Figure 1 (cartoon, rainbow, N blue to C red):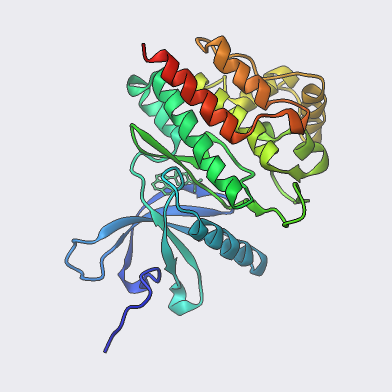
Figure 2 (figure 1 turned 45 degrees about the horizontal axis):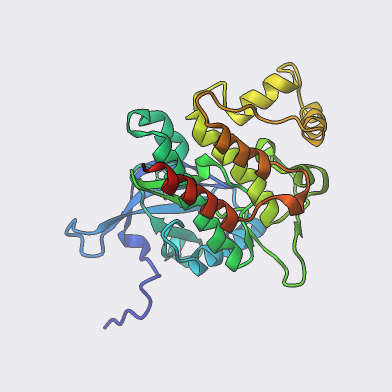
Length: 298
Ligand SMILES: CC1(n2cnc3cnc4[nH]ccc4c32)CCN(S(C)(=O)=O)CC1
């Protein structure tokens, strides 16, 4: 006898591994098939599992799952459910499978299908996803083309909410002192110096995403390569951070990509403002981008 009142619970025995897809924040995403009829008419899903798990990490994973579940938007990756694997003594996150993978990889592998109009289309979509995120007071903390997904030519979706934080109701920034490796070449100055994350710091990072888009992931032009080149490729360890901070605090910036219109570089530049409160909002950004796109079409 059987009654299914929870389609967000995926049965372990019907979830079959197909392929590995890629690493994400403290974990790993794999391509799986969910086939509860064993007739091979089921759907392909993306499944995230933790790597090197612990009690703390599992609790974080649980918060990420609830964050993802709370989100419903065309430009945010779809939550599908959970799988309580290991005879219900483990946790896995079930997500939609997006065939073209990360935007970073897609930009590199399909340059022939990409032009400025498309880049702006994606820029717009990312902004709108981020508008949506702000309505829930979620601070993403890891905006980057590696964490943006491509559904098709005409649509991208924000992913990896593994670092995402919810603003504590009475505050406008979240201070997160954390051990291990941070993606420093996407961090706002106050995130580097004070560990302070906010909607504004996501706007900073979006500026770096916009840069990424107009470099087409050329290699040698990536934020890390550029910053390291500016800082000195010799530098190791903490010295890297010291010089990046100093560099940013005194107006050192990623250069304008070759072929990038002045107007688009201006947007990057405004996002990269040391004055947190002078940065534009995601709503300002989507409107400006869409107005550029609308004014270009002729
Ligand atoms: C590479 C990626 N991926 C490649 N093909 C995919 C297909 N579907 C996916 N769903 C979620 C991620 C994902 C895919 C899996 C890992 N990430 S993440 C956001 O976890 O850092 C980027 C996307």
